[PDB]
RNA sequence: GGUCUUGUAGCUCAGUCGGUAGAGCAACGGUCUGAAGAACCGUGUGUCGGCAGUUCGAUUCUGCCCGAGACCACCA
RNA sequence: UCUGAGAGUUUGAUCCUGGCUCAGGAUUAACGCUGGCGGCAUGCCUAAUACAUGCAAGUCGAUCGAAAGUAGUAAUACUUUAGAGGCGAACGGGUGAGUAACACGUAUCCAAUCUACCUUAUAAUGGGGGAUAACUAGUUGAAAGACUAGCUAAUACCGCAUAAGAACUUUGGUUCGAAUCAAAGUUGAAAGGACCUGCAAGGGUUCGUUAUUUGAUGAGGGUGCGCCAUAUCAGCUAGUUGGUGGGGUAACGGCCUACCAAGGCAAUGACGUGUAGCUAUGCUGAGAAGUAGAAUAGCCACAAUGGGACUGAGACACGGCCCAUACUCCUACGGGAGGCAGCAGUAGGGAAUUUUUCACAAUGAGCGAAAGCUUGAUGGAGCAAUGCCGCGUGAACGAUGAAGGUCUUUAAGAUUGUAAAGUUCUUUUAUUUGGGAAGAAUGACUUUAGCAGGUAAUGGCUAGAGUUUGACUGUACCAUUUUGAAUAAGUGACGACUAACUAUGUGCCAGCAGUCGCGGUAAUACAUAGGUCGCAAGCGUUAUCCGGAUUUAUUGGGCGUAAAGCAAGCGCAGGCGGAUUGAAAAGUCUGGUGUUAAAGGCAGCUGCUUAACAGUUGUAUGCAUUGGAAAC
């Protein structure tokens, strides 16, 4: 919402991204790429979960799953 | 007080068929015009058809108009449903939630394909024993032509099977009714005397949880968002625990206001036109085509099995039948849902006739009520209308 | 609003017109003494400002201030 | 968390008995292999000061069932006074209700005890309970409730539960008392204070 | 009131009868919790008369314990 | 609620007074490579958004809808 | 007596400097993820943006004219105040925009300040008069409103009188930038009511009034003090500095006017800069301190903007008035309204922020003799896993161990797992039935008695009665009160750092990814499956304040080789001073004096079934003082 533009991490296997859509950022440092500082969440404001992250459900947008 | 609207008679959700501006809209105006002259809860209308920017001057309306006009004999949820290019959706889906239907025909402006579509669907969902009124008799020479137009409008109704010669054609001039001649007042009075007979007032029990066909929304100055619609079942009461059902995820909410067309209700019973200010909502959250319900009730759905008899082309089908990749619109009281097509076994295309048992999923989770006599059209032509059969996901 | 700042104005406007008239009737006396520097105008303005210093229309503080500064002048003889 | 649901599992790992020994004796050749899918022959090579203090905390609480924040606030309560408060806090821990019920010869089960206290079928000094977290003084009286003073379950539990000599009960009356301040010798010689007591300053 | 809701409490204080409570006060005089009205009074009762000899007006509440002080029966000497 | 606009191969996009699936990258056999680049052709896939007439035809003409992109209707 | 834990991280390997990461708490927290209760507490970071509605300050015929009306035949009784007139309107809530200041706080003085209203003390309440709002008529226009006139009240306005006193001038006498006083002059109070009494006369009570005169209170000011970054900010300043004459405040002040002099300030840092409400306090640390000044408390400001002015005790006033206006809105086009930083409520925004909730019960504020009445103060109630506390999701029995995951891949054996099944039992809660709170033991009010001048009692003082006060409540609380194991775990991680491994797939891709780091094809670092290990109606994410970070080192660091001793020197100031004498005695510390709030800390406990807490008791800091000291 400010005039600043930043790189960020497409979380995990895949994406739910629509290229000019709004979502929420995320903490986390990536030591694989230099000068990069930020992460951004899935399943948020347009996206739809990390799919079949059947061992983890926090901050994915992946709900507490049914059996 | 907000002129809390009194109910001293069972309310009926009425509507109108034919086509607007033939005297139809002017009937909606004049019946009220003469009303406040001799009627309670029965104000006078001349030009109050409208409450929207850009809608005044054009003379052909986009949106439908829910109003309240009563008498000493009947109150009416009078809805100005347009039948127009891109706007017949306003009238079509209305025929369901209008518990009555007055056919307006003009002594100046001929029956349109609008009237044909209207009567078609009115029979298809199923409503018996209509009444018709000849409007715009303000120009002379109506003694005997009102016989030939009578036989052709009875032919018009007999294409689907309402009451025929048992329904009467009251004649009258909306212009000489809007102006106020007592002999001409007697024309709308005979309209009334033949309406309350052969049209009942459907008593819907006030104990079913709730359901509402949503018609419009407003976020009133400084209190928040009010949402108006037609109560289907039961009462709506204090702070009521509610969930907005259909087409969307489920939302529980608490009310913050109620009116019947800017006139409060002490008890929004079944069949009422309720406009509820809510605790913290927005108009953008609620569109045309949505539903509401007291929870513990019908929940949203997509898939279903539908035993249906299909409208032949003569009943207004498509110039050619419909396949399985087909994408029609099923008419769920408030909305026209584009759905899949999986006809029953022993039907690849549903030719004229063909009482099928199709199975279909819908693009959004809609609260499905079994037996809901919903309709199906596409391209501007009607192919399906009937009651729900088997609840699936 | 309030019931009683509106009627407060309604009541006090005229009383303050009266204040204007009166306090002018004494400012003129001030001037006169500045010409009529004598015990007569002294007592005259004494008597007069007696009404107002007693009231709020003058304070005994400012009344005494002025009258003392003036009697200092008249003490010239 | 409130209720565990299985305790012999915990012993499997810990190799400890909530009782003297009889937590795991013989169920067709009782076998205290730690639980799971990863060890039969695999012997200790991952023990740490961190891990040992973990284990000791477990052993203590796994016999006593003390959730996080309540345990911490017990610690903190006892922090306020001054002295060699270690044994003091330990006694207080025992002066938990379910603890005293278990140690009264009347609860053969702390899982009994706490359940019973949370249902409050025990009639105390001018007040009933539904909370298993009250603390006693040396010489505090305890009585049952007529509701349960007939239950064969209760009559066998009161007949035999864990008993301290420093508590007493007239079974004739079923009425007893947390008699006196006991001694550490009268307490399980297994757990370590130093670790947990130094562990707890985290807030 | 102070204390947790469903258990009010009110320390008894000398404060101006015009400016808010918890504002600036004249003096504090013990405390009686208005929950139980049996007794919790631990008042000085000296600085009260100190105030009173040079002007003060209490609240109706205090007239109860004033009757329990018979405050008249001692301040009448001043008015005597 | 409709409309203004988007729908094509794997992505995106082309579509002679309609004629099919056509461009860029994906894409990998084979070349190289201190190792793999960058770099050379390969490739191939194609219901051309989903349904309705239709000429040696409806993907192009259109009818309807779906949803991606903009507006018209709170509300003197 | 308080009271402080470290883990790793540069290589072939070592040592050492260093960082770096990790390992904690804190939140107004927000996210995911799901989410029982009970309690306790809180709940727009945003725009001092826009804002329907209500509410958020009225009282007072016992202050009155009049108005209106009622009962009564009337006479009158009786009612309601639109109007007058008085007090409350400067309380309060919000907001902190804003400011670098005497602001905040602290010490302080006010020989230079005010303080309507109690308290102290009394002097009294004498003589008139004029007046209109109201009401009326008519004008005026749709309105906004305005305008002209007929008639009145009052404790509503002006004089008349006295004036204890008081205030002043004036001479004298007082005293350590003042007072006490002797003497002249000047000059000033109101109003009636009720109630009792008495034929009256007159008194008496009492409401109210006028003055002195205390208090008490605030307000105001002053000041040291201490209270951000900024030297990649050094000259600055003209009522400005100083003096008069005058205005002049509430009072002191160029505070202002004139007038007369040129002065005043500075690197021990002006000016300049960014930020900003403050204080108690809030968390983190062992602390100094960091850290912020969530919430709250007290000081100060602010009310749409920018101006005014009355008003009184007080505003240039957040629901005052007027002005220029922003801008919305109304109008007929002639004119106007408005200002939520009062409440909830909405819109905008955000990641987001509870009900357009009830009560005068209680507290309270006010006004009212009296009843009273209000009171989006106040108390409540409600949403929310926002925090915190308490507490669920059954107790025992019960296996070579159910099936079955899972493996081993051996076909076993185990795990899963008393966990299961199965029984005995269990009912807080789910769920009955009812009892059934205090809070009101206040307070008015009428009696009762007693008290007291006044006696002529009214009226004023003590004790009893009951009239009676509730949103809460019905609930709280209780009832071997019914049924009923019924009514109820998700969550994370498992290479090392640092707890937690089997299997698959897969092979530097996919991806993990606080740090070292795992993936280029046999993954205890990917993902899933199982298991393990973690917490639990929560669990994780993220943020930041700090711990660790003594990671600037007064505490508690150095300057040879890991930056680190400027080339050197002179060098004012400054910092830093040999010894024994004396005096002073600043610091210095002690001893005493008051202050440094509440709250909260800390400790003591009462009530919290234990709780959180709330209270309860004190505690301490420093300031300022008194008293020493002679050690430095």
Image (cartoon, coloured by chain):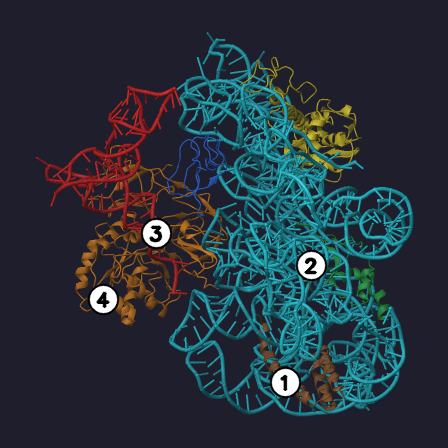
Chain colours: A blue, B orange, C brown, D yellow, E green, F red, G cyan
Above or below — where is G467 with respect to C6? above
**Residue G517 left/right relative to G265:** left
Disc 1 vs disc 4: Cβ atoms closer than 8 Å?
Answer: no
Tell me the distance, in whole angstroms, between the alpha carbons under discs 1 and 4: 83 Å
Tell me the distance, in whole angstroms, between the alpha carbons under discs 2 and 3: 63 Å
Tell me the distance, in whole angstroms, between the alpha carbons under discs 2 and 4: 80 Å
Disc 2 vs disc 3: Cβ atoms closer than 8 Å?
Answer: no
Q: Residues within 10 Å of mark 1 (few under 14, many from 20)?
A: few
Q: Are marks 2 and 3 on the same chain?
A: no
Secondary structure state at the residue bearing disc 1: helix
Secondary structure state at the residue bearing disc 3: helix
**Residue B253 left/right relative to G457:** left
Q: Residue at x 77, y 66 (%)?
A: E56
Per the rendering, the mark at residue E23 is 2
Question: In the rendered structure, the residue with mark 4 lies on which chain?
Answer: B
Q: Are marks 1 and 4 on the same chain?
A: no
Tell me the distance, in whole angstroms, between the alpha carbons under discs 1 and 3: 81 Å
Above or below — where is D47 with respect to C44? above
Per the rendering, the mark at residue B97 is 3
Percent x, y of residue D199: 67, 30
Secondary structure state at the residue bearing disc 2: loop
């Amino acid at each position: 919402t400010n005039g600043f533009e930043v790189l960020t991490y497409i979380p995990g296997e895949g994406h739910n991204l629509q290229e000019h859509s709004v979502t929420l950022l995320r903490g986390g440092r990536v030591k694989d790429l230099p000068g990069v500082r930020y992460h951004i969440v899935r399943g948020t404001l347009d996206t739809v979960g990390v799919e079949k992250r059947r061992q983890q459900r926090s901050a994915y947008g992946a709900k507490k799953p049914k059996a | 007080a907000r002129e809390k609207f009194d109910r001293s008679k069972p309310h009926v959700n009425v509507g109108t068929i034919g086509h607007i501006d033939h005297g139809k809209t002017t009937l909606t105006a004049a019946i009220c015009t003469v009303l406040a002259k001799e009627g309670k809860s029965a104000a006078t209308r001349y030009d109050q058809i409208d409450k929207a920017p850009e809608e005044k001057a054009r003379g052909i309306t986009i949106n439908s108009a829910h109003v309240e006009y009563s008498s000493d004999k009947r109150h009416y949820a009078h809805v100005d449903c347009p039948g127009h290019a891109d706007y017949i959706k306003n009238m079509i889906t209305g025929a369901a939630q209008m518990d009555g239907a007055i056919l307006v025909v003009s002594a100046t402006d001929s029956v349109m394909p609008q009237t044909r579509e209207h009567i078609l669907l009115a029979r298809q969902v199923g409503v018996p024993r209509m009444v018709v009124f000849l409007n715009k008799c303000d120009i002379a020479t109506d003694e005997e032509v009102q016989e030939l137009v009578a036989e052709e409008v009875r032919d018009l109704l007999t294409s689907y099977g309402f009451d025929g010669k048992n329904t009467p054609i009251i004649y009258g001039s909306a212009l000489k009714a809007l102006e106020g001649d007592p002999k001409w007042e007697a024309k709308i009075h005979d309209l009334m005397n033949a309406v309350d007979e052969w049209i009942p007032t459907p008593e819907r029990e006030v104990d079913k949880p709730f359901l509402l066909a949503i018609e419009d929304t407003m976020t009133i100055t400084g209190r928040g968002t009010v949402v108006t619609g037609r109560v289907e079942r039961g009462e709506l009461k204090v702070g009521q625990e509610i969930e907005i059902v259909g087409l969307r995820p489920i939302r529980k909410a608490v009310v913050t206001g109620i009116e019947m067309f800017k006139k409060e209700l002490d008890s929004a019973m079944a069949g009422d036109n309720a406009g509820v200010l809510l605790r913290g909502v927005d108009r953008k959250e609620v569109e045309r085509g949505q539903v509401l319900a007291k929870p513990g009730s019908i929940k949203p759905h997509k898939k279903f099995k539908a035993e249906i008899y299909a409208l032949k082309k003569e009943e207004g089908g498509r110039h050619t039948g419909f396949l399985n990749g087909y994408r029609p619109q099923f008419y769920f009281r408030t909305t026209d849902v584009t759905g899949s097509i999986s006809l029953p076994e022993n039907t690849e295309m549903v030719l004229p006739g063909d009482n099928t048992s199709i199975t279909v999923e819908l693009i959004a989770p809609i609260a499905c009520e079994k037996g809901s006599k919903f309709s199906i059209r596409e391209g501007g032509r009607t192919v399906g209308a009937g009651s729900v059969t088997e609840v699936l996901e | 609003n309030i019931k009683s700042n509106e009627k407060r104005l309604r009541q006090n406007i005229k009383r303050n017109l009266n204040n204007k008239g009166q306090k002018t009737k004494l400012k003129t006396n001030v001037k006169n003494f500045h010409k009529e520097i004598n015990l007569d105008n002294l007592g005259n303005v004494y008597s007069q400002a007696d009404r107002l210093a007693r009231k709020g229309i003058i304070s005994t503080n400012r009344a005494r201030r002025l009258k003392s500064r003036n009697v200092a002048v008249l003490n010239k003889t | 968390m409130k209720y565990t649901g299985s305790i012999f599992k915990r012993s499997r790992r810990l190799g400890f008995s909530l009782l003297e020994n009889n937590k795991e004796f013989s169920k067709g050749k009782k076998r205290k292999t730690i639980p799971g899918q990863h060890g039969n022959r695999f012997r200790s090579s991952t023990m740490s000061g961190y891990a040992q203090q973990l284990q000791e905390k477990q052993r203590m609480q796994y016999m006593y069932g003390i959730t996080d924040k309540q345990f911490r606030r017990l610690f903190r309560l006892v922090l306020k006074q001054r002295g060699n408060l270690a044994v003091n806090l330990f006694r207080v821990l025992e002066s938990r209700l379910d603890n005293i019920v278990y140690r009264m010869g009347f609860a053969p089960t702390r899982r009994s005890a706490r359940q019973l206290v949370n249902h409050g079928h025990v009639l105390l000094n001018d007040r009933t309970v539904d909370t298993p977290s009250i603390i006693l003084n040396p010489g505090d009286k305890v009585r049952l409730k007529a509701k349960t003073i007939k239950i064969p379950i209760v009559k066998a539990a009161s007949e035999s539960g864990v008993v301290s000599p420093f508590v007493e009960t007239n079974n004739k009356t079923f009425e007893g008392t947390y008699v006196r301040f006991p001694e550490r010798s009268e307490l399980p010689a297994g757990i370590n204070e130093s670790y947990v007591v130094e562990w707890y300053k985290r807030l | 009131r102070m204390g947790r809701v469903h258990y009010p409490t009110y320390r008894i204080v000398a404060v101006d009868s015009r400016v808010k409570r918890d504002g600036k006060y004249i003096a504090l005089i013990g405390h009686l919790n208005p929950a139980l009205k049996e007794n919790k009074c631990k008042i000085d009762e000296a600085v009260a008369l100190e105030w009173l000899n040079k002007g003060a007006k209490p609240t109706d509440t205090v007239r109860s314990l004033f009757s329990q002080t018979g405050l008249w029966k001692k301040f009448v000497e001043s008015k005597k």
